[PDB]
Image (tube, grey):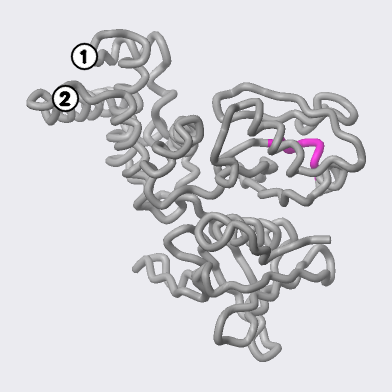
């Protein structure tokens, strides 16, 4: 079996709505090429927000996403380690700081962001920072949004949701394993009704306006458009293990203490002038961050983490700082 290909030289790409798409490649096709073909198929204007990623299945349950560079060749992608048992996903990797800005810009991309976020929320792709409290509240809106776009009833019925979709589809595994089904349904019952109580003075919440609310809750969070990396900081040729957080509100920052959400800026995206990677022992990659008014910062990282750091940093630079200028170029 092979999760990455349909066949020799035909790439399988999963969209966030469950669709699959195929791309014939030869030895010259780049990830950039497939992204442009997907921009055209899907009528996207904000392609700068999007990336192709590999889905790694880790030993314990849960997936790790490996960002792929545009200049990277598809053949070069099938040679990553155990490419055959990973999947290719098209996803928004560089989120706008306020979701509403995407909606006025590319509605297709905004709808794409809402569908991807729902999947992210239910599959616990945010940390435990997503408390069951928020998770149920998010579910009540996802549930609302699924109903108003399928039935005229503006009043939401768990019994419908139970049959048509399955309640479990809107809930994380943790609520499923920890909360009592009766307790979950009571919780949703009070929630949906209370939000229903918030709306009567107002005209009914449109699905689109509900989706805006769904993504605003998500936008105030740590792993929103962001990732956590282990890395080895080399400072005066001696080594220490660091945890980096790269995201839209953190530039490249370092986690000092999770308990107090203590994060330290190492570099705003605007202060990054270049990223360079080299090779070391046993798929260990040395990253050198060239930052304004400081000596370069040196990181020793596992190769796929090294690449997801460059991509995510270059991705947010292209988005938030300058669309033309390059910071990272593989060769």
> Residue at point 37% right, 11% down?
150
- Given residues 150 and 110, the one toward you in this image is 110
- Given residues 119 and 188, the one toward you in this image is 119
Residue 318: x, y in percent?
Answer: 58, 57
Quick check: 195 above or below 64? above
> Residue at point 55% right, 37% down?
45
In which quadrant of the rendered view does residue 231 lie?
bottom right
- Magenta span covers which residues? 82-88
- Given residues 304 and 267, the one toward you in this image is 267
Q: Indicate whether residue 84 is drawn in magenta.
A: yes
Q: Which mark is residue 155?
A: 1
**72 left or right of 144?**
right
> Is the residue marked by circle 1 packed among few (<14), some (14-19), or many (20+) residues within 10 Å?
few
Tag 2–tag 1 contact (CB < 8 Å): yes
- Residue sitting farthest toward the left: 201
Residue 228: x, y in percent?
Answer: 54, 59
Residue identified by numbered label 2: 196
**231 left or right of 302?**
left
Q: Is residue 173 visible?
A: no
């Amino acid at each position: 079996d092979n999760s990455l290909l349909f066949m020799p030289n035909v790439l399988k790409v999963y969209l966030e709505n469950g669709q699959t798409k195929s791309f014939r490649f030869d030895c010259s096709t780049s990830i950039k090429d497939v992204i442009l073909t997907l921009q055209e198929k899907l009528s996207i204007k904000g392609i700068e927000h999007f990336s192709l990623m590999l889905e790694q299945r880790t030993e314990g349950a849960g997936t790790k996403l490996l960002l792929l560079h545009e200049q990277e060749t598809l053949t070069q992608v099938t040679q990553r380690p155990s490419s055959h048992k990973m999947r290719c996903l098209f996803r928004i990797s560089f989120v706008p700081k306020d979701p509403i800005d995407l909606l006025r810009r590319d509605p297709v991309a905004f709808e794409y962001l809402y569908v991807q976020s729902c999947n992210d929320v239910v599959q616990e792709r945010f940390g435990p920072e997503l408390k069951y409290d928020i998770a149920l509240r998010l579910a009540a809106l996802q549930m609302y949004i699924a109903t108003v776009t399928t039935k005229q009833t503006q009043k939401i019925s768990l019994k419908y949701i139970e049959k048509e979709w399955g309640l479990e589809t809107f809930l994380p595994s943790a609520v499923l394993q920890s909360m009592k089904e009766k307790n979950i349904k009571k919780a949703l019952s009070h929630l949906v009704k209370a939000n229903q109580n918030l709306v009567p003075p107002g005209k009914k919440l449109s699905a689109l306006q509900a989706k805006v609310h769904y993504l605003k809750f998500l936008s105030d969070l740590r792993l929103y458009g962001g990732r956590v990396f282990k890395a080895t900081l080399v400072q005066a040729e001696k080594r220490s293990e660091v945890t980096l957080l790269v995201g839209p509100r953190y530039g490249i920052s370092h986690v000092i203490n999770t308990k107090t959400n203590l994060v330290a800026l190492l570099a705003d995206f605007s202060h990054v002038n270049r990223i360079e990677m080299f090779s070391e022992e046993e798929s260990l990659v040395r990253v050198e961050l060239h930052v304004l008014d400081v000596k370069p910062i040196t990181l020793l990282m596992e190769s796929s983490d090294a690449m997801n750091l460059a991509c995510l940093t270059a991705g947010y630079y292209r988005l938030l700082v300058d669309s033309r200028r390059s910071i990272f170029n593989m060769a």
